[PDB]
Amino acid sequence: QNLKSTDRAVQQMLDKAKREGIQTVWDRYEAMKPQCGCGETGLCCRHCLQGPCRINPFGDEPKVGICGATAEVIVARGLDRSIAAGAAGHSGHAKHLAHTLKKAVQGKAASYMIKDRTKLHSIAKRLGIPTEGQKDEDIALEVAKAALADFHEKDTPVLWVTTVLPPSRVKVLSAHGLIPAGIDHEIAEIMHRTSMGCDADAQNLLLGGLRCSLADLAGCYMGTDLADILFGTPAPVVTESNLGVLKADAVNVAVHGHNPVLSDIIVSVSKEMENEARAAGATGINVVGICCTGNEVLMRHGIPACTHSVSQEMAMITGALDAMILDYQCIQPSVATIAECTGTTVITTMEMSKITGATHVNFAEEAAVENAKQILRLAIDTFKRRKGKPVEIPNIKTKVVAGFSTEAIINALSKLNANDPLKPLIDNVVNGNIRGVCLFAGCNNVKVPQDQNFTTIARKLLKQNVLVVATGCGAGALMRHGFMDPANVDELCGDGLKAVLTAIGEANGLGGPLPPVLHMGSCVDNSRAVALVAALANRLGVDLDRLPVVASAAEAMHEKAVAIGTWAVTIGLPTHIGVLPPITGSLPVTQILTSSVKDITGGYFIVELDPETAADKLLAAINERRAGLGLPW
Amino acid sequence: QNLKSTDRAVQQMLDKAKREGIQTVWDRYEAMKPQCGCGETGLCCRHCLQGPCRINPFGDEPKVGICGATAEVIVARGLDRSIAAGAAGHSGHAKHLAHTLKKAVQGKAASYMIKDRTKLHSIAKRLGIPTEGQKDEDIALEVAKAALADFHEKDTPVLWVTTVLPPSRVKVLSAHGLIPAGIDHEIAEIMHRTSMGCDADAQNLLLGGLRCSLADLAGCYMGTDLADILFGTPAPVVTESNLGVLKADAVNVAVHGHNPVLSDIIVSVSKEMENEARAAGATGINVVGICCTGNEVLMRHGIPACTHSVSQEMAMITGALDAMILDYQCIQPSVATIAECTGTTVITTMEMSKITGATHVNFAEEAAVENAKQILRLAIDTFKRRKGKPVEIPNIKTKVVAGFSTEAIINALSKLNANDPLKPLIDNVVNGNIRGVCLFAGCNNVKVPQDQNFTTIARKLLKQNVLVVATGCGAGALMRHGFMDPANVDELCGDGLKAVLTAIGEANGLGGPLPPVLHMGSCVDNSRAVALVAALANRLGVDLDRLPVVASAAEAMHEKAVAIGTWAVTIGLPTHIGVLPPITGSLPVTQILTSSVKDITGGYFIVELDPETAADKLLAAINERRAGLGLPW
Ligand code: SF4
Ligand code: SF4
Ligand code: FES
Ligand code: FES
Ligand SMILES: [Fe+3]
Ligand SMILES: [Fe+3]
């Protein structure tokens, strides 16, 4: 079971699933081997009904697609479509938040409001909207309008790109025509240009993909902005993670997916429903988190994270998960089938995200509170049905310090320097206490023993004094193995990093260091790390491709992770990916993505499947950046 | 060679290609056999980096994707993405025309203007824009604004759907939530909902696809509207088709692709460049058409159609094709490679559609005339280089009567009834002289002997008195085999159809019938057939799913054809497809698309690979519609 997951709680539930005959994601993976190699390397195209066209990576015919598409055109078109799909996900999430905010301030959805008015005003200022003498409702209306306008062409380019990166970075990108004109505009142009008999030049196609990845960044940054306005900017919190946060005697309710628009309501509403839960024989309602909507409510409310990504089925295998409340993205549709074995009530809430066999509750922001109680009453009912059943919850959980928004990080640092908060961080980079910064992002992947790449790479960077930040299921992986527990700083961190984390923590009244890894939130909250890195660049007066900052999508799965990896490259970062993206069938495309893009954006992909080697390569990229600034390393 | 193409000119050029060693689309197809069956049936998914997930159509494991996605979810997601890609193509084309028109009336592009002011006023009226007391420039500005607004969410749904179908049809579609909210909005939502861990219910997914197909119809109808305003509504024309329209002693210039924004300029500009061509030793510039941009200039100017679709390479094999001017869509990228063997200058003109090895001229509407002369001078240069070379142009061509816009058809019929022009058509349907109407649409496919399905089905419907209309490469197939020559009416048409075609032709001063098949234009001009069918429904006071009208994508290839087939079903038509779409791996999806969608929209797919059987099935669908209206059959 160790070959499947490094998580001990997951290993325990795999044994339970095996002996009960419940098929898991790892069993379905085993049944899929040997997997198709052509697809695995990108050398397959089904973009017209003359296909499928497959090209063998090596040997004899076929060597080109039926229409004449070369290996490099086929690879580049496939990648562009996956970038577009990721952008469509992150941007659909942000779009729903934009409508939610507009409804809130237009009197239509009273469950929603401007919770962070400071953030609302900073956003409108960054965008050029008038704060002085305006009602907040009017300002927010304008912010929601600008958000929605960024999806289509207009007289300005996408503002959630051009106003969030330094002007020098926007200049480099404009010179190559990489600034998106509109988020859904770019998505559609990708789908056009990659369709049969259209763009057939690898470099032309990949430049389009870089631009579409920036549309994805815009949607990430928009999603983070709008959720912070609506639900509050995260500040440091203390909670727990892993399966042991489930409680046999409570109504256990998982919130799962990405969009917190209803799950934030679930959180507050469940608190009111406590006595109804006690009346049913439970101690209360225990809301827990799965995947990114779990990260959202962890970041803002301290909701414990139950599990993540590849291992999400294992929460139900405990037999104690009474409800799983779903919005969209990264939900294994197998949960609907597994629910008949485990008694879990699986509920979908989003019109465009249903699963055959799951109960559907038509969530509307206008009825959110009523929708929540209906869903939670179903969870209470399910708890009743299992009264007296035995459950198997692994008694395994870790302590998690999280809530490090960029505002929270700046405030932590400001306790060492009130009017130049970034200076103590830069000082410690300059003097070597902080070698550099690494962002871990993205998913788990069934092909990688769960969390193995995240923890292996994390351990080696921390020993080398890298400041490590994390989002999404990268944060999930690190949090479930103790990397967000300050009591582990001594074991994990180099001497220089320990001193800095300790200096900041002791200045924030903690009497203990910051945690070894800073949890910056969900997948769209990768945009928080961009805001921190951009503010660092603006403070140093250099572009991002000169900073000792790198990114690692160490166990990437989703098309969203591919989009994120691509805009990290596009804004200038060396970007590790720890799973093979479908590009190895074309050396020209690989050479563009890992070498010659350096001369366009300054960033580049690092494809490395061995986690110890990936750590060496990330350190080398960090150190090259250090030497380029004249620093020691 | 007969197994490859039923076109004798194509067969002759295949022999030339074989003996010169030039590899063709049919050779590349042969090298691809046996093709992957899983892909061919839809049972493959690469929507995340855990894949590819393939399911065998029959037998043992694997039976589900790694994430739990069933065969029916995988099939439905793949189809939805192909519908989205088609919509992205048709809508990108329309979007470029919208910008071209706005530039024209804003004084920025003097090569462009309002050529059809009657059409401009009818469009603004259909949309609710004020004609009275407004400059045409102001009206056109508003029309272009409404066009661009239909790409994103707003207070109205997509007007190029809701204002072009009968209100009863819009009502049926609204009741199922099928009206698009915005063209690129729907494209992106498809890419979201089909990404990993999102929509996982076949019926939910296919309803989304129906709605996205209507976004494709909107883009088709927008493209036709804007091109008619800019370049004139087609009226009946006489020309020729097939390779024999090339002339050894002229500068032969093919316009190839879909968007006529530059090719219409090529047409008029080439006329001015005649003496420069004579000075070079040519008789002049012989502009000819390939694929849909060829259909555009044929419909409006009588430009001869040289060839279409699967056989486009064969035009260059003559050795007489001096330039091939490309915009986007359905261009085999092999033309760039074949050009080094044939001396052809291949020129791309669109920023998002380049081909490695082709000369690129950066067309801008603001410099269109200058761009045209530069491209045409290159064609003159290439003619010079081949002065004295032998060429092999097959002396094979057919006579083509075309230009039957819906306005042209209504005007033809109005010579039999001036103030009720649709009545003579309906009368002859009622009394049986016209059994019904069939629209042939879409591509050639290398898997089908070129034109075999179009002509076989056409021959049997015409003998049964079906009024046959055609667009795109369906029109190309029928025109190259004599189906647009009135001299063939006697051979091809039933007695009832002959009498009607003769009655209309003799009323239009022709002294001869209309041609056996009415050429309604390019692929976006499938929207013309919708306008005719909707006007027929509105005249009879019934919905489209009660009319004896059917559609046949007899040799479908492109994702655009899949979108078109799907919106024909969605507006209510029995819709034949003569190539296997990737759906046979899921019986539930097949059953939805061919049977139970009947209860939603009234239309349905007819999947039939044998052309004689497909003809019987189309006739049966026509006759069922006849009996439902109480008519004899
Ligand atoms: S677009 Fe080209 S390579 Fe792709 S399936 Fe069609 S013929 Fe094959
Ligand atoms: S989305 Fe599901 S079925 Fe598709 S490749 Fe990923 S794991 Fe496989
Ligand atoms: S041949 Fe396997 S992915 Fe297409
Ligand atoms: S396994 Fe052949 S299309 Fe994927
Ligand atoms: Fe996740
Ligand atoms: Fe074509």
Image (cartoon, coloured by chain):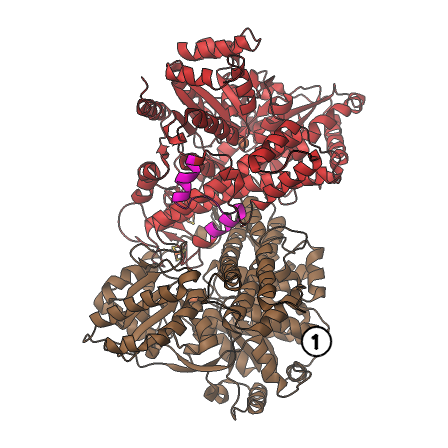
Chain colours: A red, B brown
- Judge by depth and name the residue closer to the eye, A170 or B283: A170
Residue B154's x, y, as percent?
65, 51
The answer to whether residue A267 is left or right of residue A610 is right
Instruction: Say if B41 sits above or below A545 in the image.
Output: below
Q: Seen from this angle, which residue lies furthest left?
A: B388
Residue B623 falls in image quadrant: bottom right
- Looking at the rendered structure, the kind of residue marked 1 is Arg
User: Which quarter of the figure has residue B28?
Assistant: bottom left
Q: Residue at x 45, y 22 (%)?
A: A2
**x, y percent for residue A414:** 53, 16
In the depicted structure, whether residue B489 falls above or below residue A265 = below
Please indicate whether residue A353 sits to the left or right of residue A485 in the image: right
> What's the chain of the residue with tag 1?
B
**Does residue A174 show up magenta in the picture?**
yes
Viewer can see residue B434: yes
Q: Quadrant of residue A542?
A: top left
Give the quadrant of the N terminus of chain B. bottom left
Q: Position of residue B135 (x, y in %)?
A: 61, 68
Q: Nearer the viewer, residue A229 or B145?
A: B145
Give x and y (percent) for residue A599. Answer: 32, 38
Is residue A116 visible in the rendered structure shown here?
no
**Residue at screen point 78% across, 20% down:** A278
Q: Taking B242 as reference, is A283 above or below it?
A: above
Element carrying mark 1: helix
Tell me the magenta residue range: A168-191
The residue wearing badge 1 is B539
Q: Main secondary structure of the magenta part?
A: helix
Which one is in front, B437 or A154?
A154
